[PDB]
Image (cartoon, rainbow, N blue to C red; front, side, top):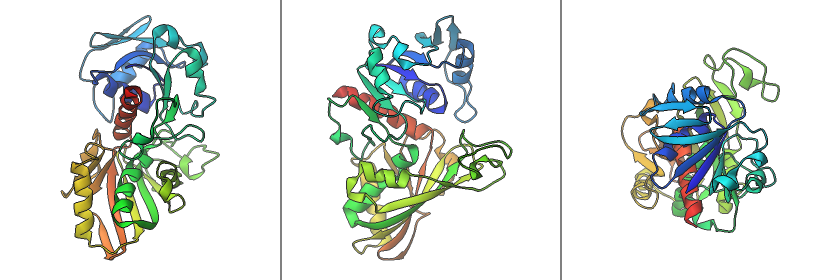
Length: 331
């Protein structure tokens, strides 16, 4: 599979790290109109959260070069002007968050790419979550979306719980690490007043659609889940706090066994399970979409339970993007 990456923010860079480790993926090009090759090489190489790239990174006038792989770079504002066809690009991966609808992402196809994978939720493009609805993908679909990181954490667990005990209703809280939209000291954030306030000295309440977005990937849960978020001053790794009213009576011990079986079975690698005394930093660079915290969870009555699942909001999601990429080309 020959891929190009559009955008070089958190998602863009990490998708590149992971893609470069996939033997069947070839990373042909990178587009980012707002950085030069030396800066791109720098940004890729040093990471405050995930460490130094273990390998040699450098650049010339037309490439970022990593361990012998030259990756051509482009500085195009309009993705239509990109030489994807001429470069024979199987899949364009859009990590910019501004080409995320069927008509806007279409520009990569126009430019020559065969398919597009979008690294944000979409209104128009069909959404997929590995281990949730990937079978529902079909080869004629040219533009898909990988949903969101919080969605990738909630959906796989929610499916497991609903299939096994039924979800009548659920209210979710995500305790979320800092993100790039936040400010270092109280600053302007016109659409999201709270999100403008000093990131590292606040618990910051935030609205999030990810809980209803489970509705789109699992239609059987439409309108049964919503939630909210608290942004806290950790730099990465977030956790889902799911308060769910069940349909069938069950022990907590039974929930544990069902989830663990799913972790070891069909959801291996997407959904994880632990019983150990873990904290957020224990999940830095973990590639699971969702890691179930068995000890942190608490059951009140036999149909009323609180489930806790971790996710590295940057790395898990980025691995899923690459998973979706390989899956979509396998078709």
